[PDB]
Image: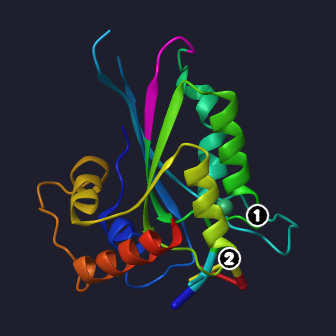
DNA sequence: ATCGG
């Protein structure tokens, strides 16, 4: 029930400038009792520390660590929606671990909305394709998703969502890139 | 300004 600072949101989820951090706004909705809204929240990655020897944990793994805390009923079907700053990586095992989670728990269906494509990982295409081939929806965040996260996850205090310059442009471009990757 | 130093 603790919301997100507006400057952090507009700083990390900017699809024009790529940040050195990753945030993840997750929703968990029950499907068919009646369809309900059961869990919402957000988290961020754990920064890698060279001096202490810590390699860091990306936001996807940070969410996979939280799944036991959700008390998901194995008899019902849940839809998990991600609004992640960077697309999940491959070289560091995130896409593989998410695919592993999706295979053990077939009652959970995941859809991922990425604000930016993590093309720093040379195998980002293999990550997105692996996520698609595992039954998870892979999409790029558009204005509707940014405004949604602003209205439900951000402590806006009544201030409406003011889109940054190039939101629709970069969102369309990344949508085209992802459409070209998932062929 | 690409999961940070
Ligand atoms: Zn990762």
Using the image, name the chain to which the residue with label 2 belongs: A
Can you tell me which quadrant of the image ligand 1 is in? Answer: bottom right
> Mark 2 or mark 1, which has the lower sequence index?
1
Please tell me which residue lies in front, A23 or A134.
A134
Disc number placed over residue A69 in the picture, else none? none
Residue on which disc 2 sits: A121
Q: Residue at x 47, y 74 (%)?
A: A180
Q: Quadrant of residue A173?
A: bottom left
User: At 28% from the left edge and 57% from the top edge, which residue is drawn?
Assistant: A145
Q: Look at the numbered disc 1 and say if its residue's Cβ is closer than 8 Å to ligand 1.
A: yes
Q: Residue at x 42, y 70 (%)?
A: A179
Q: Is residue A83 magenta?
A: no
Tell whether label 1 touches label 2 (CB within 8 Å). Answer: yes
- The magenta span reads A74-80
Residue A161 located left or right of residue A30: left
Q: Nearer the viewer, residue A93 or A55?
A: A93
- In the current view of this chain or complex, which residue is farthest to the front? A183
For the N terminus of chain A, the image quarter is top left
- Residue A136 visible (yes or no): yes
Instruction: Describe residue A29's horizontal placement relative to residue A73 as left or right.
Output: left
* Chain to which mark 1 belongs: A
The residue carrying mark 2 has its beta carbon less than 8 Å from ligand 1: yes
Residue A14 seen in the current view: no
Tell me the element at label 2.
loop
Q: Position of residue A146 (x, y in %)?
A: 27, 62
Q: Quadrant of residue A64?
A: top right
Gap between marks 2 and 1, in whole Å? 9 Å
Determine which residue is flagged by label 1.
A92
């Amino acid at each position: 029930r603790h919301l997100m600072d507006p400057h952090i949101f507009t700083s990390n989820f900017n699809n024009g400038i790529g940040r050195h951090k990753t945030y993840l706004c997750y929703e968990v909705e029950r499907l068919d009792s009646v369809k309900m809204d059961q869990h919402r929240g957000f988290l961020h990655n754990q920064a890698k520390n060279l001096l202490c020897g810590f390699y860091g944990r990306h936001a996807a793994l940070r969410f996979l660590d939280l799944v036991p805390s959700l008390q998901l009923d194995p008899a019902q079907i849940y839809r998990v929606t991600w609004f992640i700053s960077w697309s999940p990586c491959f070289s560091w095992g995130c896409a593989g671990e998410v695919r592993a989670f999706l295979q053990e728990n077939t009652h959970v269906r995941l859809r991922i909305f990425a604000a930016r494509i993590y093309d720093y990982d040379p195998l980002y295409k293999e990550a997105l394709q692996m996520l698609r081939d595992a039954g998870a929806q892979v999409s790029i965040m558009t204005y509707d998703e940014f405004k949604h996260c602003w209205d439900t996850f951000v402590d806006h205090q009544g201030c409406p969502f003011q889109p940054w310059d190039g939101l629709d442009e970069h969102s369309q471009a990344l949508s085209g890139r992802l459409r070209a990757i998932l062929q």
